[PDB]
Image (spheres, coloured by chain):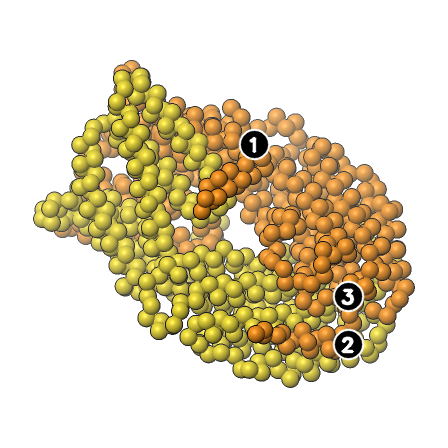
Chain colours: A yellow, B orange
Amino acid sequence: VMRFPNKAWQTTWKVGREDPRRLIHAFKVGLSLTLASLLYLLEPLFKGIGQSAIWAVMTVVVVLEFTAGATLCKGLNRGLGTLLAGLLAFLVGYIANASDRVSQAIIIGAAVFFIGALATYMRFIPYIKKNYDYGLVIFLLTFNLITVSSYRLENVLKIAHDRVYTIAIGCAVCLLMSLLVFPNWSGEDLHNSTVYKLEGLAKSIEACVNEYFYGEIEGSGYMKLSEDPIYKGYKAVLDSKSIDETLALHASWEPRHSRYCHRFPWQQYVKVGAVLRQFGYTVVALHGCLRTEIQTPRSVRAMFKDPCIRLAAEVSKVLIELSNSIRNRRHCSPEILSDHLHEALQDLNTAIKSQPRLSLRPQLSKIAITSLEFSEALPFAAFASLLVETVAKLDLVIEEVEELGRLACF
Amino acid sequence: VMRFPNKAWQTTWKVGREDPRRLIHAFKVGLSLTLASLLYLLEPLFKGIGQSAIWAVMTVVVVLEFTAGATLCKGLNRGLGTLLAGLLAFLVGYIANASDRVSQAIIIGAAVFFIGALATYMRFIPYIKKNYDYGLVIFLLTFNLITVSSYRLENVLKIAHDRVYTIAIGCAVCLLMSLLVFPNWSGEDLHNSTVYKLEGLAKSIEACVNEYFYGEIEGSGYMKLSEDPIYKGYKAVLDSKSIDETLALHASWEPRHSRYCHRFPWQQYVKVGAVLRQFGYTVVALHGCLRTEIQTPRSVRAMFKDPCIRLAAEVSKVLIELSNSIRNRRHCSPEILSDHLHEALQDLNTAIKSQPRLSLRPQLSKIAITSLEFSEALPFAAFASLLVETVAKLDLVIEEVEELGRLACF
């Protein structure tokens, strides 16, 4: 326990060093909250609206999002959600307070119940559970907080359309401190997520072909994929579907057209993200192939250290020449795929041709498998087939990235 | 657009048919919200606390969670979060209102700012972004809503420790309508997530070995993995890490010991979930192997339709005999791994022995690969190696599930 809190300093700097913007965004949100709350003192003038200041702070806490685009997409989304909920609440309240006491009680109760049922239900729907989840958490909260105002009085509507002015001051501070201070344009954050994916995926292929051929120690059963920086690299391409999707959305939903880009192509980046997702499924197949129970003997696995190491180096070289292409906004070399790549594949083909033979509770199945003369190099043949499928996927990725370029300025 | 809303009826029943409990939980949350809000009318007696009723409703909306365990884990978590935030706010308020006007303004502003900075920052930390995210969203909201009370008056503390009684009525309704009405004990929801994983994974292996050998049509490049029910099966084992982790937590955090289970083993289920995650990485390697660009010829792929189909059938049979074992609470047959499995592997080995040879913009790399005489059956060799690694992983899964049984009553 002594080292738990201080050890946080190591978790905290990862957030710090991995990305410095998060610090700037935190200081943003802070200065925004404080500037909005400072309605505390300014009430004596400026129309005496300082009493409702809290709402400005809450608005900054709900609308302001890290990516200046996101703080506008969800901004408008939470806004209509709350406006729709408020309209429904005002409706149920006007229909309420209309019949006698027990009548209004039954109507309010049935409305709140029906609504909450529907609300949690929709919460279960996985279309609006991870995204637009705020669409029903806010919906329900606003609706109940307005149904409670129904009972009190109707001058509450007056005071609400008054305090809308300060909720607007809060929204304006959010908009400003998100777009015109040190914005994090989500578009151009999906213009760098791609280069990160490509760089990390090249790193992952190189590191995979290394930890297999110059094996740390051949035996598998050491730990979870998470600890090794290889998973650090290809888990992104594993799960970035939603990330890239929401990024492309927010970006398309961002105002800046100073790109001097004929047509804002923030969908082609999702195309490239999908191609990379497929390439990453392949790389994950690789990393699995290096942690199998039935494993090829190191010795028999040595005669190939020559060809596939070079082949993986060429795969990573082409992937990195693509990563430089999205980052520096230039189309790839026509001959990106090298004569060196084809030479490496020729060499690997030859290698395949040369020598073409190709208390404790113990594991019963492994014994069965290895007792059978299933080719000892069969796992390696699987590895090599996966590596060659990687080489093939390279062309698909190249075509998609070049279409991307042609789509953007590039 | 005409068919968009009605087509929701198809999205809605999936939630309905996939699991009926969600309906019962929705009606729970609804009856709870309404019963709490019904403080509206009961104020004339019962100590006249009906004015703050809203807070009971909000408490039911925040604490009540689908899994009776979760509504207690996050319940206590959100509670100390809000208590800590309230303590910090009362501190900054007492230190506030202590110096003169501009002094209190500067202190309140610096406190709110510093706090929001820290809060959004911590929000970025991915330890408390997906889980305990409510730990900082609530933290910040409560802290600001208490800093706004600081300015008003100190009798607010009186009224707050009064309205704590009705927030307690709300919490009690949540606790009751979550534990003693139709509870969804999260533990025993991680006792069925396992059987679902195993059943679906057997289905996935069978369906994979089928869509390759009796290929729909061999060519790949049809669509995203998501549409085919195979991804429906193995994406769970892909991403269930966090799901199983939080489930085991909540379960360990559940009160019922009527299990008559010597020791509540809600970690061994996570062990089994990890073994299944590895098995599922292998199955994902398979499904990749059936959607490769470089693909084995169907003809050359026919001579093996005999052995691996039987081998995959035996893999799925053993996986399903395990799924029945966790579901019916009995240890597996000592000889779960069949003589039929070993016979299938012998046959596949023989098969490997027999015939041991083993405007449009066109894709340049594929041409290079297939022009080279890389073995046409090399992709199939990779497929077979993956299938045999599956057979091997079977023993690991068997050992983990049997340890599980021995851990629980079983």
**Residue B290 screen position, x and y as percent:** 70, 59
Q: Earlier in the sequence, mark 2 or mark 1?
A: 1
Q: Nearer the viewer, residue A197 or B212?
A: B212
**Residue B177 screen position, x and y as percent:** 47, 26
Say which chain tag 2 marks. Answer: B
Marks 2, 1 in one chain: yes
Q: Which residue is mark 1?
A: B20
SS of the residue under disc 2: loop
Q: Are marks 3 and 2 in contact (CB under 8 Å)?
A: no
Q: Nearer the viewer, residue B66 or A130?
A: A130
Amino acid on which the number 1 mark rests in the picture: Pro
Say which chain tag 1 marks. Answer: B
Q: Nearer the viewer, residue A98 or B81?
A: A98
Q: Earlier in the sequence, mark 3 or mark 2?
A: 3
Q: Which residue is mark 3?
A: B297
Outermost residue toward the top? B45
Mark 1 or 3: the one toward you? 3
Residue at 69% of width from left, 42% of height from top? Answer: B199
Residue at 23% of width from left, 46% of height from top? Answer: A167
A62 relative to A352 in the view: left or right: left
Q: Which residue is mark 2?
A: B373
**Residue B164 screen position, x and y as percent:** 32, 29
